[PDB]
Image (tube, rainbow over all chains, first blue to last red; front, side, top):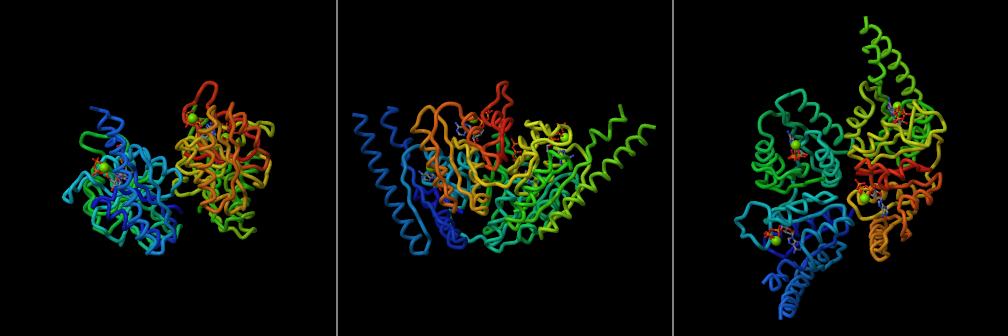
Length: 261
Length: 260
Ligand SMILES: Nc1ncnc2c1ncn2[C@@H]1O[C@H](COP(=O)(O)OP(=O)(O)OP(=O)(O)O)[C@@H](O)[C@H]1O
Ligand SMILES: Nc1ncnc2c1ncn2[C@@H]1O[C@H](COP(=O)(O)OP(=O)(O)OP(=O)(O)O)[C@@H](O)[C@H]1O
Ligand SMILES: Nc1ncnc2c1ncn2[C@@H]1O[C@H](COP(=O)(O)OP(=O)(O)OP(=O)(O)O)[C@@H](O)[C@H]1O
Ligand SMILES: Nc1ncnc2c1ncn2[C@@H]1O[C@H](COP(=O)(O)OP(=O)(O)OP(=O)(O)O)[C@@H](O)[C@H]1O
Ligand SMILES: [Mg+2]
Ligand SMILES: [Mg+2]
Ligand SMILES: [Mg+2]
Ligand SMILES: [Mg+2]
């Protein structure tokens, strides 16, 4: 099981770096650390000796990238993790998505270099990656935190099924029980969803419990997540004005989130 | 890994039944066998009527019970942990619902409606592979052990899913994988091939590559032996002349593993 950590070396990415290393160690899984030299920054001179200016900027960005990679590589080696570092140039989300094809789990921070420590939202690189990634994406808040619990938003939709299947191995390897949350006005429908997810988890060596609720799903999922709880759910598709369930959950999440498509 | 075998008890489903049991045994994986009482058949009388429908459902349900008992007996004999499930509704619908709790589906290419000379795909198999959330393995009627594996890889999203789905299977079976990447640009195809080979090796699977040009479907079809598991992404659109996967799946000579 290959873990791919994407980091821009920013404070907001520190939690992701720590979590990826912690997971690699706990799961005895190899870790690939990726830093992308942002062409959107290097191209600024062009949007305005432009080739020279662009080269000078790329050189600075690449050197910063090498420093970040070396720092994480050093940390990972110290932890006893089999780590490899990759430095590429391009649009961050595109490069990350390309490298994701060879990974089994991605770990990114909620935000990065562009936002201060007061930002509770999601950066655009993280947003674009989770919406198009072929493999599960784990978004970690800036402040490092261990995964001490797990909950799953399950409505039996295709993506919820993928989230369910993606979560099982992680919960199993970490010894975490999973709280299945199924929300619907029809209690019989929600119950059927919950029992299904619980059966799957138990069949895969994971303890599970369920909460069959009515009302607003996003609100319930957000309120039930503790700072160390991994909240797993299907990734959003449409970009709704008021936001779909997953959009509202991911934007306001207090703890680590695992998305799957 | 939970394997879900869907069978209608027909001769065309015998291959899938055998393969599912064989895989469960080889991987020490639990097996669920599902038979669906087809409401499309039971409801024919609706075209009193309720009594006639009930009499047909009763017959269909009893056949299903017999099929499940036969398969369960075989599996239990091999030491496989098997669960039997009797459902009623539209086959592909019930199969797709049950798939949400499985990690791999095993179905025959065709079933009860076609003779032993049909090399095509039945509508239940078609609908299931196109909408399944988990990998679907389509097995020919004649039972055959998987003795090899090939992967059609063009780095597309579904090809990536197929690649990730195949790895655990090839590993457990000790089969090497021949990666086939096709494109007019040799460099692009090689990059694709190398990417898949690297993933497979990183997951304990030996791999080789065939970088080709020309028609992808033709190459994939021609390279598949009767015992080779051909893994590829499931089709999306229903093209008039058929997309690559549509053509491969329709004419495949051996077992196919689809993912999406
Ligand atoms: N250049 C990069 N290289 C590698 N990973 C990156 C890069 N940029 C962002 N990431 C990953 O995406 C996560 C979110 O960063 P993101 O760029 O989306 O937020 P932001 O930088 O604060 O706002 P924005 O980039 O939209 O202006 C980071 O914590 C990191 O894991
Ligand atoms: N009622 C619910 N109960 C529990 N979890 C839910 C519920 N609704 C949504 N979710 C979670 O959120 C994920 C995505 O739901 P969401 O409706 O936001 O995406 P979508 O429906 O697939 O795309 P779209 O917003 O375009 O319809 C689901 O896969 C599931 O994990
Ligand atoms: N009633 C059923 N219950 C369980 N599995 C089924 C059922 N019907 C079909 N299947 C699965 O689907 C595979 C393909 O059968 P399919 O129904 O698609 O071909 P067919 O019956 O010959 O043609 P058609 O059903 O379109 O008239 C079967 O081998 C079996 O694995
Ligand atoms: N050039 C190729 N080389 C190797 N394998 C291929 C190639 N093209 C397609 N495939 C295989 O066939 C699968 C599906 O390809 P296909 O083009 O038929 O589906 P699609 O492109 O995703 O949907 P659509 O036909 O609507 O565009 C891929 O995931 C891949 O495994
Ligand atoms: Mg950024
Ligand atoms: Mg929805
Ligand atoms: Mg049929
Ligand atoms: Mg295609």
